[PDB]
Image (cartoon, coloured by chain):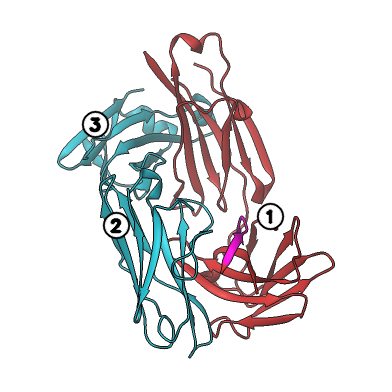
Chain colours: A red, B cyan
Amino acid sequence: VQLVQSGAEVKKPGSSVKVSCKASGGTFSSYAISWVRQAPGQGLEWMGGIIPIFGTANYAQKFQGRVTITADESTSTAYMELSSLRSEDTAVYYCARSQVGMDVWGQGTMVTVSSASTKGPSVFPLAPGTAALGCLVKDYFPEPVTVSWNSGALTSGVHTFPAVLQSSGLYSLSSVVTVPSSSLGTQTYICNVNHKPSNTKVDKKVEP
Amino acid sequence: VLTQPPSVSGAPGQRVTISCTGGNSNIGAGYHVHWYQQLPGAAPKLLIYGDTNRPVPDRFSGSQSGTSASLAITGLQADDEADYYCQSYDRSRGGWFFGGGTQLTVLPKAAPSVTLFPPSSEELQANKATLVCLVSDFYPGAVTVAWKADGSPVKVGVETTKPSKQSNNKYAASSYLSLTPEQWKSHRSYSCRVTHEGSTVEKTVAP
């Protein structure tokens, strides 16, 4: 079984967001689906839950009046709608199945509540018995971006560092890879950056 | 509702015990205590359920007494460093609520490796300049980063990250100095200094 969730979203303070949670095999309805948020650096917060087959929902007192948990047994998809968003709601929202203890969690959906606007990155190449090359993913918003090398063929010596929120409100990240110096002439190294919030994908070749 | 120690640490092969205490409305009165493991940058996983049952290696175990529960990890491994959350049903508030979480750390000091990248030619042609000082493979997390242009401390344009955890249980970090092409060309050298447990590594680049 697997629980798949909708993509990351950017919303402005006061708007409403709706995160989905579809099943990939099982009796989605006879189980319960819990929704739990986690803010950056904080712990888990049980927002609520629902048993679909019966249609019955429960909400923690904290998010009561703002959160609506619904479920479809046909599509086997739960939905959590949060209204009147705030800067503090910015967090990753997980859905977790549990027979009616949570044993099947989802990948999590990042919901960013900020009056800013989504922007794609500028990917610059950082040129070099060991040389080190890399890629600088600058001036993008919001988190996250994903970086691979040779489309995944290169994993040896790869290090993707955490981003930094620049004073401009845009993030900047770096991913480096250490390689033999002698191979710099023959082999080709390309970093593949993907920023799904802005639907950007860039394959930048790092040349000496 | 549930109280957890903010952090626990132990060397490889040791037995660690994380506690989770509440009142008679949650852990007391019968309601079981679940234990979840969250690895750096991942979704939680169910370690223990029903106070002592496993879905999970035998090294992990759980116990419950009175208004307290405890998770025991024997033969500590590097893969065990992670956040541990205890969950229980509160009867007064009527709902399943987590604890503060415990950051289990698996422990030898280690000085950092620093790599300084100067601005790209393309970036300079894009009316931008960014020097990148990458730090890796240092334990503990504490680390200071300072920038100097021609020996004068640069304090404007500096953006540094807080030490994050690597996959090898050590730490990494990154610092960025933002300049205009003319600023970068008007000095003869820039340098980043990474201080860690009294030992500083300094790297320098020059136009």
Residues rendered magenta in the picture: A102-110
Of the two numbered discs 3 and 1 in the rendering, the one whose residue sits closer to the viewer: 1
Instruction: Give the SS element for disc 3.
Output: strand
Q: Which residue is mark 1?
A: A2
- Foreground pick, A156 / B26: B26
Residue at screen point 43% across, 29% down:
B119
Labels 2, 1: one chain: no
Residue B16's label in the rendered image is 2
Q: Dot 1 falls on which chain?
A: A
SS assignment at label 2: strand
- At label 2, which amino acid type do we have? Val
What chain does mark 2 sit on?
A: B
Residues A15 and A156: in front is: A156
Q: How many marks?
A: 3
Residue receiving disc 3: B202
In reply to whether residue A108 is colored magenta, the answer given is yes
Q: Amino acid at mark 1?
A: Gln
Q: Who's the residue at 22% across and 40% down the image?
A: B108
The amino acid on which the numbered mark 3 sits, given as a three-letter code, is: Glu
Q: Quadrant of residue A104?
A: bottom right
- Horizontal side, residue B175 vs residue A192: left or right: left
Few, some or many C-alpha atoms within 10 Å of disc 1 (few <14, some 14-19, many ≥20)? some
Q: CA distance from mark 3 to mark 1?
A: 48 Å
Mark 2 crowd level (few <14, some 14–19, many ≥20, 10 Å Cα) = some
Residue drawn at 39 percent across, 50 percent down: B80
